[PDB]
Image: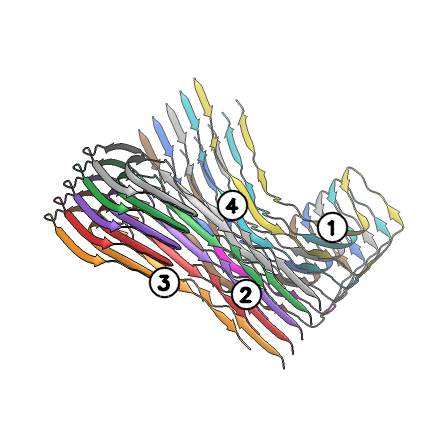
Chain colours: A purple, B red, C orange, D green, F brown, G blue, I cyan, J yellow
Amino acid sequence: GSVQIVYKPVDLSKVTSKCGSLGNIHHKPGGGQVEVKSEKLDFKDRVQSKIGSLDNITHVPGGGNKKIETHKLTFRE
Amino acid sequence: GSVQIVYKPVDLSKVTSKCGSLGNIHHKPGGGQVEVKSEKLDFKDRVQSKIGSLDNITHVPGGGNKKIETHKLTFRE
Amino acid sequence: GSVQIVYKPVDLSKVTSKCGSLGNIHHKPGGGQVEVKSEKLDFKDRVQSKIGSLDNITHVPGGGNKKIETHKLTFRE
Amino acid sequence: GSVQIVYKPVDLSKVTSKCGSLGNIHHKPGGGQVEVKSEKLDFKDRVQSKIGSLDNITHVPGGGNKKIETHKLTFRE
Amino acid sequence: GSVQIVYKPVDLSKVTSKCGSLGNIHHKPGGGQVEVKSEKLDFKDRVQSKIGSLDNITHVPGGGNKKIETHKLTFRE
Amino acid sequence: GSVQIVYKPVDLSKVTSKCGSLGNIHHKPGGGQVEVKSEKLDFKDRVQSKIGSLDNITHVPGGGNKKIETHKLTFRE
Amino acid sequence: GSVQIVYKPVDLSKVTSKCGSLGNIHHKPGGGQVEVKSEKLDFKDRVQSKIGSLDNITHVPGGGNKKIETHKLTFRE
Amino acid sequence: GSVQIVYKPVDLSKVTSKCGSLGNIHHKPGGGQVEVKSEKLDFKDRVQSKIGSLDNITHVPGGGNKKIETHKLTFRE
Amino acid sequence: GSVQIVYKPVDLSKVTSKCGSLGNIHHKPGGGQVEVKSEKLDFKDRVQSKIGSLDNITHVPGGGNKKIETHKLTFRE
Amino acid sequence: GSVQIVYKPVDLSKVTSKCGSLGNIHHKPGGGQVEVKSEKLDFKDRVQSKIGSLDNITHVPGGGNKKIETHKLTFRE
């Protein structure tokens, strides 16, 4: 019972950006107010939690391109 | 019982952007107010939670292109 | 019982944008007010939750193109 | 029962950015106010938690491109 | 029962940025105020926690590109 | 007798190929026979001769693109 | 008799190939026979001769692209 | 009789190849026979001769790209 | 009779190859036979001769790219 | 009769190869036979001769790139 598996994908891909100018961004929000009340906290096992967050993010990449490639060969029995 | 599997996809793809100018963005919201009250918190197993969030994001990539490619060969029995 | 499987798709695709100018965006909302009251929280297993959110997002990519490609060969028995 | 598995994907990919100028970013939010009250905290097992956060991030990469590639060959029995 | 596994992926990838100028970034938020009250803290096992944080980050890489590659061959029995 | 000659041709040309897959070429001619009889050969001055040849050529370039350019400026008086 | 000659050709040309896969070339001719009979050979001056040849050429370049350029400026008086 | 000659050609050309995979070339000709009969050879001046040849060439360059440039400026009086 | 010759060609050219994999070349010709009969050879002046040859060449360069440049400035009076 | 010749060609050229893998070359010709008969050889002046040769060449350079440059300035009076 011969089994042959050949796995050779070829990727010549290209994720590209060109910008001539990326300027004059202004991020001036007014002041936020967050008031969170939790009487008891009791986290267990796998938990990711954000309580009372005020995030002011300015994210200006000249690129920002991305490429996620996943390869997976699975030979069970 | 011979089995042959050949897996060679070819990808010459291209995700491209061109911009001449990317300017003059203004992000000036008024002040937000969040008030969340939870009497008891009890998270378990796998939980992702956001409570009381005020997120002011300015995201200006010159590109921002993306390419998600997934390959999967599965040989069970 | 010979089995031959040849898997070679060819992709010369192209997801492209051209813009001459991308300017003069203004994002000035009035102030929001969120008031959420939950007497008890009890999350279990796999849960994604957002409670009391005020998100002010300005997303101005010069591109923003995307390409999701999924390949899957499955050989059961 | 001969088994041959050949795994040689070829990747000549390219995630590239070009910007002529990336300037004049201003990040001037108003002052935020976060007030979080939790009567008892009791975290267990694997927990990631953020309580009372005021994050003012300015992230201006000249690039910011990324490439996540995952390869996985799995030979069970 | 001969088993041969050949694992030789080839990667000639390239994550590249070019910027002509990356200047004139101003990060002047107003003063934040965080007040977090937790009556008792009791962390156990694996816990990552942030309580009462005011982070003012200015992150301006001339590049900022990244490449995460993961290879994994698993031969169980 | 003022003579001004400005010779500035501008060339942004582009000779491009994209081939996803180029395979499975078989060049299997039958055997040939060449018989040339002569007695005298008296070549002189500029002679490019070729007598009694049997060529089998498999020429498979990945692009094989050509660009031939020729600029001449001649000036007598 | 002022003579001005300005010779500034500008060349931004581009001869490009992209081949995803270039494989499986078989060059299997049958055996050939060449028989050339002569008595006198009297080559003189510039003679490029080739008598009785049997060439088997497998030429498989990955690009094989060419660019041939020629600039001449001739000036008599 | 003032004579000014300005010879400044500008060359930003580009001869490029990208091959993902270049494999599986078989060059298996049958055996050839070459028989050349002569009596006198009387080559003189400039003769490039080649008598009775049997070439088997497998030429597989990864790029094999060429660029041939030629600049001449000739000035008589 | 003032004569000015300015010879400044500018060359930013680029002859480039990228090959992911270059393998599995087989050069297995059958055996050849060459028989050349002559009586007199009387070569003189400049003769480049080659009599009775049998070449088997496997030429597999990783790039094999060439750039040939030639500048001449000739000035008589 | 003032004569000024300025010869300043500027060369930023680039002859480049990138090969990920270069392997599995087999050069296995059959045995050849060469038989050359003559009686007199009377070479004179400049003769480059080659009689009765049998070459087996495996030439596998990692790059094998070439750049040939030639500058001449000739000045008579």
Q: Secondary structure at mark 4?
A: strand
Q: Which residue is mark 2?
A: A74
Q: CA distance from mark 4 to mark 2?
A: 37 Å
Q: Which residue is mark 4?
A: I16
Asked whether disc 2 touches disc 3, contact meaning CB atoms under 8 Å apart, the reply is no
**Residue D4: horizontal and vertical position, in percent?**
65, 66
In the rendered structure, the residue with mark 4 lies on which chain?
A: I
Circle 4 packing at 10 Å, graded few (<14), some (14-19), many (20+), is: many
Between tags 2 and 3, which lies in front?
Answer: 3
Q: Quadrant of the C terminus of chain A?
A: bottom right
Kindly identify the amino acid type of the residue bearing the numbered disc 3.
Answer: Asp
**Residue I42: horizontal and vertical position, in percent?**
81, 46
Q: Residue at x 51, y 68 (%)?
A: C8
Q: Which residues, given as a range, are shown in magenta?
A: G17-31
Using the image, tell me which numbered label, if any, was put on residue J57.
Answer: 1
In the rendered structure, the residue with mark 2 lies on which chain?
A: A
